[PDB]
Length: 104
Length: 103
Image 1 (tube, helix red, strand yellow):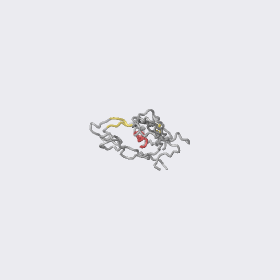
Image 2 (cartoon, one colour; image 1 turned 90 degrees about the vertical axis):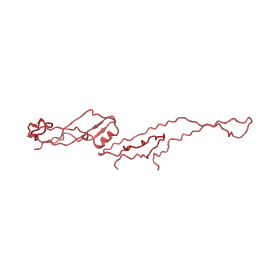
Image 3 (cartoon, chains in turn green, cyan; image 1 turned 180 degrees about the horizontal axis):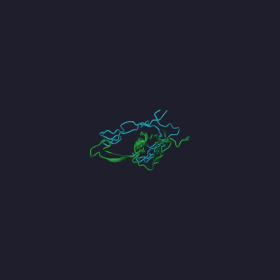
Image 4 (cartoon, chains in turn red, purple; image 1 turned 120 degrees about the horizontal axis):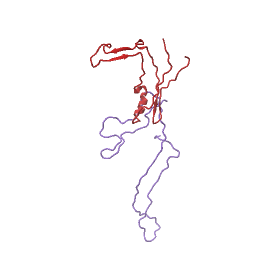
């Protein structure tokens, strides 16, 4: 309660053959569907054609999405990667969630 | 003042000449120095290897910097390349001050 869970790491490290890009952010999670799983379809979204027709479910869960290059690289880091390297690929990922507060 | 590194003991001067080779001297002694020589010149290769120490850039800037780049537009001839006659030419003077740093 009176002690932080983690620190703010948000910088890249270049070790010649590899680069480690860390990126911390602050998030907010509301309560979705008022805690209910609701069945959704193209008819609930206001109907559609047959090409846009669907059937799925909404859930009360949120999800983290860091699947974009700008969440990891800064415009400068990206330029330092683009001008000097011929290829690149990801090797390992390390996700961490901390400093949680549940406001009411 | 012209740029560069001021050195108290700079790379020494490598001096080189062709050793004289006299043409056929008289058959009777003449105290005068020989002024007739065999015309010659020398050729060959020369290598010069220099090791430079670098100081890598650790900029923590956010937006992109100013890099030196060959302009992407199409030209008649590539820059820093030989023309259609085999004559190499450097189109512009390139300096070093591209990357920025705080004061």
